[PDB]
Structure formats: structure tokens, C-alpha cells
Image (cartoon, rainbow over all chains, first blue to last red; front, side, top):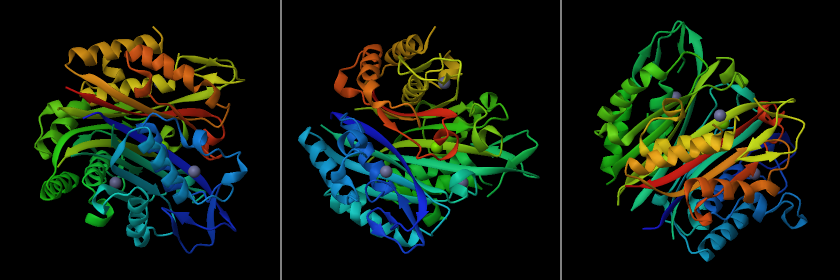
Length: 158
Length: 145
Length: 146
Ligand SMILES: [Mg+2]
Ligand SMILES: [Zn+2]
Ligand SMILES: [Zn+2]
Ligand SMILES: [Zn+2]
């Protein structure tokens, strides 16, 4: 009954000449997310929520933007290592919920695929993983398609 | 078997619309474009998220939809334990309308006032929210199977 | 048991001429927040939220005193705090060096074991007012039980 909650936030710039990879899904698009790793904004947000619930710090502490080993890193592999460290700390994951905010492209056709990727990576059934997709209703840099934002929440139990 | 969900919503403030937040009509020169009840939408998504049922976009006034959301959450074998939320609006003042929002939500979710919370914030005049171009709502929901 | 969750948000403008205090920690920087401790307000708000006692505006000295009073009110409402998690979004300066001090400040104020308090740091990847260093945001989540 020793439950804990975590929350996560991530954002990356949307630039030409990068792969667009969200929830481990490679999505056809003229632009992609800029970062040190594969820049998977959704997976990073979830990774942060998990480290946070376990009180193990954050993704920057565990997988630094200034370490060559993670240059172009597969964020699913990073998520699986996160889950491993959370389990090592003594916690089991109960559920994950998340939101993705993007003006474009359409993400609804890819949501189930993202959900399946996360569930596999966390060794969870599909019914304990949720991914929600939204636009920013034309507001701000997100409305101008300058970047894509992700949010996450995770429940664990020690 | 507890589960948590998180919700986010934002809508533009436009002329010629009534301002309805948490089912409360608030006297204001502009309203949300979408009834575009940003708060109820954020709570709805948090509940769908906790029950792992997807989102509003996949599922669908906003009170009728929240009542339906709560129905589908119950359908999946989940009971709602609590809701917490935040409204971010630079204008107008939300303080006098909070208690009514809470009452509306508690009624729609078949919950005691005890387990529903609504919080109000400005955006310190920063960004589009600060300039009164939109209103953002955030929500968190705990459920049990 | 009777678990409840809360969430919190806070932002403050970042301008030269004021000190920078995040999580009860003064941080050397050319700008500060117009004590305006974004981290502690968000956590305070999350706690009132979980307890269903309203918000910081309804209830309320620097931000640590307010956090301390918040926790006393949560306790008397019949609730015990299980854990807190949070994120600070700030383009500059580097916050990672100061996380353990913040965690110590928050855990002391809430009378929690250190391993039940977490603080994360992000930049906004140069996007929006946050990414231009015009403001700093904090987010919080708190789990409580009655
Ligand atoms: Mg935001
Ligand atoms: Zn990232
Ligand atoms: Zn909406
Ligand atoms: Zn504040």
C-alpha cells in the first residue's frame, strides 16, 4: 500500500532533417524533433514521471544531454532502463497516463502503436497504459508548430 | 487497484461567446471557442486517462459529456476517488465562481464535495494566457478498480 | 485506504533586479522572480488540492512558512502526505546542482523522509517565454491518504 505518484513534462523543437519519433513510433513527416537522443518527447515525459514517482531524480540525471553514449539514443531503450532502475529501487508500476500536444501531424492514427510500445517497454498490459493526443487550439509556439509537448503521470507502489 | 490520470485543455477567448467554466456562466465580454468548457474537458480527459479509455477526441454541453465520461469509467469497473484541478485565466476573477464549479462537478460525477477540488491562478501576464488570449485547465484524477 | 491525489501549477516573471529563490534556495543569477518561490507554491497548491481544501489563494512570511502551515492544515483535515513529485522549467541557470538542497528544504517543511520528495529540472528548449528566460514555471503532484 506504499503508493507513489509522479509527473513529467517534456518539449522539443520541430526542425527539418530529423526523424519524427513519438512513443517509439517513426511517423512520416517533413520535420522531426531536435534533441540529443532520438528526442522522443512522449517517452521522456513518461521516463521523468517514473523517476519522479520513485524519487530517483530525473531523466537529465540518469541520461545526460552531455554524454556521448546517448547521442541518437533509442528512447525506448532509455525507458526500459528507467523501468529497470525503478524496479531496482523496489517499485512496481501500476499505470501510466500521458498527453501529446501538437499542431501537426495528425497523431490519432499512431496512438495505439505508441500505447503498445510503452506497455511492452514497461512490461504492462495495454489496459494500464494511456496516451492522449491534442492540439494547442492554435495558441502559442505549439499552435505555430515550433515544437511538440508531452505530459505524463505515473502511479507506482513500493 | 488504484490508477491516476492527468488532463490538459486550452481554448481561445473570442467575442460573442458566453464564458462557461465548470458549468458556470461567468459575466465576461468574451467566451471560449470550441460549449468549450476547458475545465470540464481537462477533468474528462484525466478520468478517461485514469481508466485507460483514451481521450475526449476518441470518445466525442460539456456537463452531459462529463456525465457520460463518468458512465464509461464506471462501465470499465472503476470508481472515482477524487478530482483536483487548476484553471489558469488572467481575467476574469474566478474566486467567486469556484464553489459552484465544484458543486457542478461533484453532482455530475456522483461524488461528495469532499472529493472535488478546483483551484484558480493567473499567468502573471506571461504568454498568450497572460495576454488573455486563452484559458488553460489542468486536472488530476484518482480512480480504483 | 482513502488515497487522494493533487496537482499544482505556478509561474513567475524572471527579471533583473530581484534574487532567484527556488525551493527555498537562493541561486546566483542576473535575474530573479517578481518571495515568489514557484516550486513551493506549486507543491503547496498540490497539497491543498489532494486534501480538497481549496488553494493557496483561499488560505493565505516566506513560501516555506506557508508550506509549513499548509501541511499542518492538511494533517488536521485528517490527511497524511505520502509523496511529492515536481518539475521546474527554467532555461537558465543550471538547477541540477541545487536539487538536493531544495529536496532537503521541502522534506523538512513537510516532515517527510527524503525519499518521498522529488524535484526535477527542465529547460524549455528555447521555446516561448520560458525558453527566452522571461519566466520560470513549476509543476507538482502530491499523494495523500486519510
Ligand atoms: Mg504548460
Ligand atoms: Zn526530451
Ligand atoms: Zn476542450
Ligand atoms: Zn507563486
